[PDB]
Image (spheres, coloured by chain):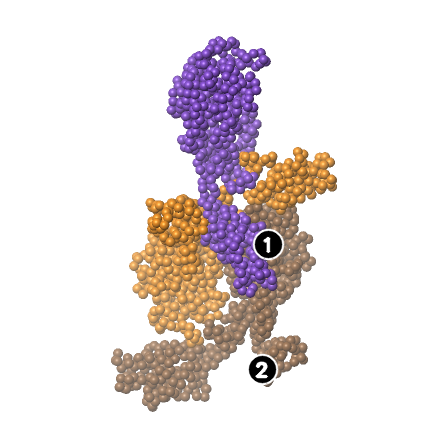
Chain colours: A orange, B purple, C brown
Amino acid sequence: TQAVEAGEKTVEQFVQALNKGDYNKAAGMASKKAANKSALSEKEILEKYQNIYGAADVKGLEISNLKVDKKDDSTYSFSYKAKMNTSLGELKDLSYKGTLDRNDGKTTINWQPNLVFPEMEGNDKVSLTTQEATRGNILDRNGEPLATTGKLKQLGVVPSKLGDGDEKTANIKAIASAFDLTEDAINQAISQSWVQPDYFVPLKIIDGATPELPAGATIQEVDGRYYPLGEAAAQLIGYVGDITAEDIDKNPELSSNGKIGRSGLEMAFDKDLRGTTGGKLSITDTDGVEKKVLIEHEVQNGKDIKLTIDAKAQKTAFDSLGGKAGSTVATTPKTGDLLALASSPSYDPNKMTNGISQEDYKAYEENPEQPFISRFATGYAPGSTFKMITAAIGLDNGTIDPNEVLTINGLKWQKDSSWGSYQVTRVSDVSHVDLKTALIYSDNIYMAQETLKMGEKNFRAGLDKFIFGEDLDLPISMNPAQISNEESFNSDILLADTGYGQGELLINPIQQAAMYSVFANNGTLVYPKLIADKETKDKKNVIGETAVQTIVPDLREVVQDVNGTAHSLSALGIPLAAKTGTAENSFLFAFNPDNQGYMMVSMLENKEDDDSATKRAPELLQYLNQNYQ
Amino acid sequence: TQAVEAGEKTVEQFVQALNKGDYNKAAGMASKKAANKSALSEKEILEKYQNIYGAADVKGLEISNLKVDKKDDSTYSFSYKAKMNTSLGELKDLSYKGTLDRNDGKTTINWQPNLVFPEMEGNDKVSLTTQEATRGNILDRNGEPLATTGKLKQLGVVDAINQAISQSWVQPDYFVPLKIATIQEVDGRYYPLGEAAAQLIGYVGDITAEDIDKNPELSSNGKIGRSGLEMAFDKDLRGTTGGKLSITDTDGVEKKVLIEHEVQNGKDIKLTIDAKAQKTAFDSLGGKAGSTVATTPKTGDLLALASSPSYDPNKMTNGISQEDYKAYEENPEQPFISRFATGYAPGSTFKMITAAIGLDNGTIDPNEVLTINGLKWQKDSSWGSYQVTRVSDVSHVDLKTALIYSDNIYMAQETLKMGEKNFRAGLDKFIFGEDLDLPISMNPAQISNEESFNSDILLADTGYGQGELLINPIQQAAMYSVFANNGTLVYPKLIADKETKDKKNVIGETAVQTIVPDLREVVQDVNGTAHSLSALGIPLAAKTGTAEKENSFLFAFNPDNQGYMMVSMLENKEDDDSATKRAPELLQYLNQNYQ
Amino acid sequence: ETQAVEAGEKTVEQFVQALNKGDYNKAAGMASKKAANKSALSEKEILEKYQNIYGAADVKGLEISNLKVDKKDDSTYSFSYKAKMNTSLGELKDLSYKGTLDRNDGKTTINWQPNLVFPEMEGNDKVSLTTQEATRGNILDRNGEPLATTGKLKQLGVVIKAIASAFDLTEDAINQAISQSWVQPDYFVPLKIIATIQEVDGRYYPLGEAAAQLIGYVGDITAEDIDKNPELSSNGKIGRSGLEMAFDKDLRGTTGGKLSITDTDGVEKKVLIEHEVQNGKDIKLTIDAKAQKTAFDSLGGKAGSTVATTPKTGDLLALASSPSYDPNKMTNGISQEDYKAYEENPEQPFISRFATGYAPGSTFKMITAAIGLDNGTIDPNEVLTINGLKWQKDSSWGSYQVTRVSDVSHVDLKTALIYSDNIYMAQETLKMGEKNFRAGLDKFIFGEDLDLPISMNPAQISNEESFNSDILLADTGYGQGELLINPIQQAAMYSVFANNGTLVYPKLIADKETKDKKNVIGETAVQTIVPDLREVVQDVNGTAHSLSALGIPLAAKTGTAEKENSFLFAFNPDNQGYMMVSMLENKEDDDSATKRAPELLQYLNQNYQ
């Protein structure tokens, strides 16, 4: 039994040449072609493996229970169990068996087609099919689609069925108008390197708007990814891209023909949404008639994802910013439900996914207001809106007497002359200011002073009860909120600018909504929620019931009182508590203090002359007030 | 200069390393990474080519109009035109440009992303999509489908119930397909007439790796015609795959399309087959071995091509049990054979051909009566044991009587009376030796093996449809059409749009006006061999036939309107079974619908 | 009400407003002439009185109230107001000014007197303004030993061979020092802290580089620092990093000062402001200075990190980082040569490696296994069969293979911990899947910020709310992937093994109270894995078997993250008295955290029970 173990080594070498895909080395180990030896020549054996093992991406072949036993002086029979990896899964418990040829202490394999797959015979062959999966939808709280995959009415033109110089130039005129698109863009489209004369050339995607078509112009139906709210939810939802080689490197389970999320929720949930590809590996006879199924995995289409977003609230919130720089966030404060996450400016995510001209694309990329940013997750100084936090702490720790009246003269202030030229400024020269007056007029000086009276140690003990430094259990990329660029202020100037929402504070609009929810839950903080089925999470006693019952009445008066900063909202006739804000940027906070049915946080970045968040809030506040009670 | 041609060599070697897919060698010719040198490390470059040139299967890169000039001391610029092959087509007149770094005599390439494709930049990428085509249908003369691709109700579960749930791949909660408690809707190829048109239409199989070797323009996910017409027209039916090669930014947003070939779905193929005639024709063969062909003889239109037994093409294409498959393969009556294209002896039916030849050249007088005794006959005793046999012992026998009773002996005697040379001059006006312009594989029809009969016995057996004649059922329909066209022969037609082709004066107008009346009498007259068809009440001309196990034949057509013709054959008949006994249901169909 | 009264009111208010703007010349022009019944000084002498006095105290922000203006006779009106003002030492409140005005043909002027500088001043009275700098507080270890202190440093110097070889310098440095621009022949030249030596007050860090990154260092105060914070004195030191900067306000104290009115000889007559100096507070840490010095030296100057705690309370006993810098030269004098060394060194000694996020490496397997066992996916006894050193789910994974180092065929959980079997865990993770994996990972402290005075990013599981790959799911199960946990965060997560599944948050301030997070992993997962963690040591094939020579009760797990990062986790399973997490970054050939762990494990074992 040295010949026996020489036969064992011969099997193992064959198998290892296969694992390295060295199909030529393995074919070199076969006996000559003969009725009693190998069934094919060496090249005929090389080809079978390249075709079948190449096609199925066979590797990771592991044999077990190897047995080699003598039949006659020049013939040894062998048998082993094997597992192998294919590109569709793992094949487990294959029973291979064959014979070996001993001829002058040289041992080869009597190759037979049943050393590709156990049951194969003669001219049998192997087929490998895949069924790609269809991408799941993204839905709002009421099932309305925000990202959906389906048929799309696409527009295009044929260059030949268009004319010459006479009609080619006026049909361009004709189809350019019917569909609101450049007459020049039609000239650059028809003249790209790829455009043969008799091709279909794509121009636009359309939605229940197919007019009587000019001549040359034909529309065809395309499967595509579609975003019904377009740019109104583009930063939240994201867009999907073509799959590349680089994507398949980083993840070779993807197929070249899919789509892949590149930003927003499309990327955050790409595995759930993309599904799993179906596939089948079969042994067939010489005509492709299946004789044995080796692997069969049914396609699983992608899962639907349901959000808390209200598509109407979303559209309205985004339009109300009129294309200026800014962001709006709205919630149902007692549960966390995020009803709208708007950011302005924005981009047309339907073009990024289905085709965008080099012109429209360079528009977006260079625009200095930066439409690809998710401003509702960008950190900002919250602004003087923040004063209601400082005040809530003040009252909690005893520092602030609601009735203590301060006397303040002018618009500038400093603790003493040691602050040099740094002065807290305010906008309204009120002399006698208690808490109520300070919220109503947005009095930074009042708050600067009550902070310095309270001290770093007491402020941070209150601030610390919120969610600074945390990461929020949400599928949106965001840095946590900081108090300052370090672990302590080491200035009274900074301690004080921070008491009125400036300084080195960074809180993004989603985080602000979370902090301010205390005013709608008796001091308990309720965490923002974006996936509809998730459970509500809270943090109790963040501030006290009595700070809230003191501050909310003063926040109603920011609206009702004629000197309130948000008194333009009293015309609406709806119950509002609010605080306005500015940082050095315009801010608005508001919620319904009668039913706590809704809360919103709106921001206008680099406000234009006399523009403000407060001027843009009415249409959304009317909507939210009516539908969330 | 030495340094300029040093640069030309480096370009030519870089490009030649790319063709050879030797991407490691090519990145090894690059300069160090630097703002005025190469933009990436050696392995970032090895990977970029592997990803992109590997993905698109770039090969066959051919450069032309190479130019190399010195720009400054340490840097030489190059430019060339190129074309290259991708898996989607050929890229033509790409304009490449770059620079080289000569540092102490050594020439490296200042690699930049525009040495993959001219237009690339920075972290740009490449996407490559395909759209596979939908296979066209095969349609009957009325647009009804004989082969169609669509949705199918696929029964399954999450005897054969037990062998299914227990195959290697069947894990617990999988859907396991049964045949066409849970149903799912799946795309597949489907044959509405099932086995009744199987040998004509064919069936399709999974595409295999072996198929992609012989034709790598195919996709792994298609189906492929394996026999019959599915295979004859596989290219027209399968269409062409769509494809797109794009340069994209780092997020997959398209910036330039290099190639776009739009999908072309497969063409429909429209036949002359009448699906109802085909089902009836096949059903009437009662599962026996045999064949039916029906035509509209004045145009050639092939209304039906039946062969029995047959097989279930829906099982070969979507799933067949190990038992059912071995049944078909081991069955000795051979269901996979297309009997309507197989050559056979035409049998005593053929006499109406001989008789027509006789009347054209003068050998046969319609009224001359022969005298015949018994059921056997031979020229003289030099024939050993070979006797022309007949079934009916009629004494006096002219031509009409001979067609009516199927009198082999009469036709033998008139054949010898005509002789090989005059017999062959008539036969040679037909379609022996021709190939018919039809998408069915078939051997041309022969008269005998060698160009003479070389026996008198064989000359006589040929006069009554035996011997070494080989005519497949379509070829018979073609020859026998002379009796519905005043002597003109009309070639069969199977593609509905093709034009009719005829061959005039194959037999004479008078042979036809003499024989057809006699063929009406094969039906009406009570001693006629096809009397059982008078029961139906339709205008028929017919001739019955036998060849020797024995094979039964029927030819028939409507002599009032020439609307239809049929040729039916029962291979190795059972006792008292016959083609004529099986023909009524199709004659009823044809008579009503073809006028 | 009268125009003459309200003209007098406005004449006062403008006088005050000119002073507020430091427009002292404008204000003296509103004075009456110099006379026994008008002003006491000329317009020039008055301008100078304000420049001296109001200039010295940086008077500004003067606010009056209760203004009263009354007729005395036709040309004389008396006035009075209360005032508050800002000085450089604070705010003066309830000042009572009084004087008279001169009406002379529609023109109203001020009959100036010295008591319109400060209420009580008279004649040639003057003003004094003194300050007292505070002395900086200490930073202390758990036993009161100083980590940062202010005191007297034996600075050595010269007014060359015999004094370069006694205290040990480069005789070159003695030539470059004496020959600098400022060195007059008769000056003292500072050379070293420990030829004449004198006693100097200085900031001193006794552990030097062993704690440089935690404690930080202090710098000169510059003009720019006082802009950003003009409550600083020109003469202090200021923390530039570490706790020196994190706690600089508490450490620096409050400067004392006194504002006084004096007679012309400096005899104090009225004290306006007096704030007594407040020296800085001491800050007391959980650090153990011996543990810190030992932990840092055991890293032999290589890149790496040691973190040690008492897991049942969070106390951080050591936070060492290597390589490091000499904070004593940064604070008291450093050659341009040594300074360029630090800033250009590529191993980055100024980084706080104990607060840097890293992939935790294969040590992480014990977290996965705990989750695996809590949710049922993993049966401690189920044996998997694994062949070779590489593995992948199927061929759709391309070139990504989980690799391991020891080719064991049969492999249950115990065995997988003992040999560090990456493949066993890859499989057991895929078997439980992202949703079950993350339900465990989420009960820990990903995303949280730790209530600590050290700047650090929170720990992530991956970059998005999901992996979007099976491959990444698997690399994460054995501590690779997109995991980021810094050594302190590692110590906090691994504490579950010393508290029966309850997680105890790190503490660096000694008096702060302990905070935990209960039922993070299960009591039975802990009782299953610790026995396997003793054998990573005791068993001869365990990856840490070289520590059984020490003779101490250990549970441990080793780790690798692939350059090559070496990891050791270890603690006492009998008394839970101490835990350590050490990391050797970019290991050399055959070096590892485990080989460098013995002297710290000996100290900790005996001192923390």
Give a yes or no on whether discs 1 and 2 share a subunit: no
Residue drawn at x 47%, y 53% as measured from the top left: B248
Q: Which residue is mark 1?
A: B25
Q: Does residue A175 lie above or below B193 as drawn?
A: below
B61 sits left or right of A355 in the view: right
Image x and y of residue A514, in percent:
43, 58
User: C93 or B44: which is nearer to us?
Assistant: B44
What x and y, as percent, mark residue C110?
A: 33, 84
Indicate the chain on which mark 1 is placed: B
Badge 2 marks a residue whose secondary structure is loop
Relative height, residue A325 to residue A128 (above, below): below
Quarter of the figure with residue C175: bottom right
Image quadrant where residue B170 sits: top right
Residue C268 in picture, x, y percent from top left:
45, 85
Secondary structure beneath dot 1 equals: helix
- The residue labelled by disc 2 is C183
Please rate how many residues cluster around mark 1, counting C-alpha atoms within 10 Å: few if below 14, some from 14 to 19, many from 20. Answer: some
Could you give the CA–CA distance between mark 1 and mark 2, rounded to whole angstroms? 63 Å
Residue at 41% in and 63% down? A382
| Chain letter for the residue marked with disc 2 in the picture | C
Query: Residue B210: percent from the left, percent from the top?
Result: 56, 39
Q: Amino acid at mark 1?
A: Lys
